[PDB]
Amino acid sequence: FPTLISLLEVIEPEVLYSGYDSTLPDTSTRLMSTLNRLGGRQVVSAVKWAKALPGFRNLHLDDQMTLLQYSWMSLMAFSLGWRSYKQSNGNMLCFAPDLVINEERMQLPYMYDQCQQMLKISSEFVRLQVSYDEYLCMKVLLLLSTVPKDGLKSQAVFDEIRMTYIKELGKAIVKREGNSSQNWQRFYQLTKLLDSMHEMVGGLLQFCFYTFVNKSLSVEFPEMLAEIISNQLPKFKAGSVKPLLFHQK
Amino acid sequence: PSLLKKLLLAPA
Ligand SMILES: CC1=N[C@]2(C(=O)CO)[C@@H](C[C@H]3[C@@H]4CCC5=CC(=O)C=C[C@]5(C)[C@H]4[C@@H](O)C[C@@]32C)O1
Image (cartoon, rainbow over the protein chains, first blue to last red):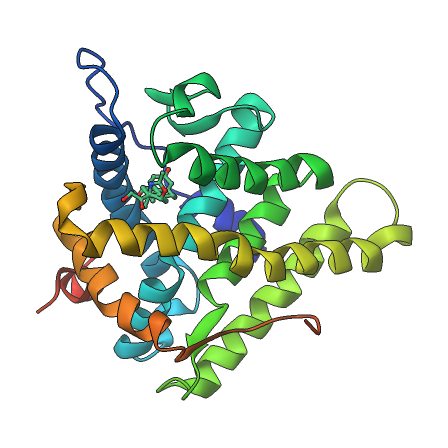
């Protein structure tokens, strides 16, 4: 019988190439615009992933939109963290197979602090030695971990799917090779990591919001990403969104 | 009418 984890492995999108043009000198504006073009295409792939994620399309369409609009940066930063862990052990930001940013290439204006925060996310995978199946279950949980304070249109469906994936993360921990001796400690550590992602991504989001609204910086955004940010930004800045935390703050 | 809604509604 096929398992839900086996399905998460099969539906995970292939890694995209950027098409970065190395012939021009790096500038913060050009690099950020290139990263946003790659990000918009990664978000398209993440939407197709969510459509294929078992249970997700049973949500009301407005809730599917809300969850993707609220969680997109968490999903992208978590996956960047994973690729940087697998490909460089957290030493370089592995945005794409043709766009790998090492510590020297990140000393451009504005870039350094944001890039260090993205490396911090990847360092958590190193510290915890996260398995691929644990990563896949946690990534689903990030899609399901930011909601309106006023609730969702299909709340009972949402509560059921979120509980299903919480159980799946448990299964991924139990199926790591070793014994059951450390399974509660592991679940505690990975849910502490999930809770920490809200803060770790929050600064990335504030930076993205500033580069989006301040047109004088000349950072380009592709169309679907601009639409998503335009909807997400006012809700986040007004304090109308809440993270679903596993632990007391 | 948003691009995200069109993609969510489109056949896979
Ligand atoms: C230095 C920096 N540029 C950002 C901007 O605000 C530029 O306007 C912010 C966080 C970045 C995103 C981080 C997550 C990510 C992973 C990927 O592999 C592909 C692209 C994204 C989704 C990034 C890009 O859009 C660019 C950013 C929004 O920090």
